[PDB]
Amino acid sequence: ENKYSRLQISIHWLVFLLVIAAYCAMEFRGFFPRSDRPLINMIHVSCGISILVLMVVRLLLRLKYPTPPIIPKPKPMMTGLAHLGHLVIYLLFIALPVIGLVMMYNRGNPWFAFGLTMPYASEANFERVDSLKSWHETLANLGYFVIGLHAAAALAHHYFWKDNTLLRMMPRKR
Ligand code: HEM
Ligand code: HEM
Ligand SMILES: CCCCCCC(CCCCCC)(CO[C@H]1O[C@@H](CO)[C@H](O)[C@@H](O)[C@@H]1O)CO[C@H]1O[C@@H](CO)[C@H](O)[C@@H](O)[C@@H]1O
Ligand SMILES: [Mg+2]
Image (cartoon, rainbow, N blue to C red):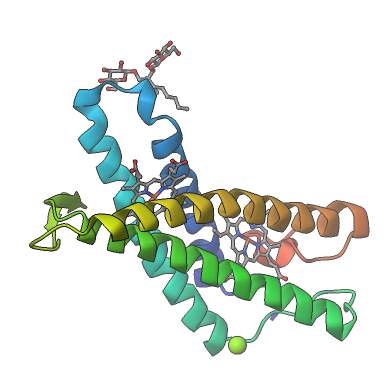
């Protein structure tokens, strides 16, 4: 009816938590000794892979289900634009972890996700890694900005315009 489905709400906020954890693992890496870095890297990649899976799943749900309407109703072009913004989020947060994965693959070393050993190239590819590393960094930085705009828009809706944009994405009926 008037909310996203409970599964979509769960996934939205789960991904938020996982993204926070992914960023935090990288941002605070140097606060841990060298000896803990493998674990920090594992947390990072494991969150990243979880996020990728959930980004794909949420997108398939987005196709399957209607978008709940906003009350009052935006102009059709405003909805189009918000929906375009969403497409940009879907793309960014799929491309970011994919680049991560391809980076780890092309490094040609054993690596671990969810306590499990993952595939890697039998020979390393250094031109590719350098480029992938640069892209991962840029997209991760673009991610901050995009989440910030995204959250800010939600807050402008909820507090300034006083519409139900954010309530539709919140778990409780309020
Ligand atoms: C939404 C998902 C993810 C986010 C937000 C994210 C974010 C970041 C950030 C902020 C950094 C530090 C970049 C910098 O130096 O400023 C980073 C580094 C890294 N990420 Fe991710 N990441 C994600 C997914 C992944 C995945 C899935 C993998 C691997 C499977 C991965 C592997 C790495 C690696 C190896 C580095 C270290 C680069 C280096 O030290 O040479 N990331 N990530
Ligand atoms: C405090 C943080 C956040 C707030 C307040 C927020 C708010 C919202 C709101 C209000 C919507 C519904 C928008 C609409 O229907 O027009 C929504 C949907 C969405 N949000 Fe967020 N959000 C946050 C964090 C995130 C993060 C971290 C991501 C992705 C990494 C994200 C990705 C999305 C996507 C892709 C949608 C479209 C529906 C879906 O697939 O779940 N959000 N968000
Ligand atoms: C919001 C992110 C906060 C990051 C905190 C990182 C954490 C504590 C982790 C435990 C957190 C408790 C809830 C790692 O510190 C320890 O963490 C242990 C983890 O078991 C490691 O085994 C141990 O070797 C490491 O030193 C604190 O370390 C930093 O603390 C600073 C003073 O605030 C120090 O000036 C800084 O220089 C140090 O580096
Ligand atoms: Mg649909």
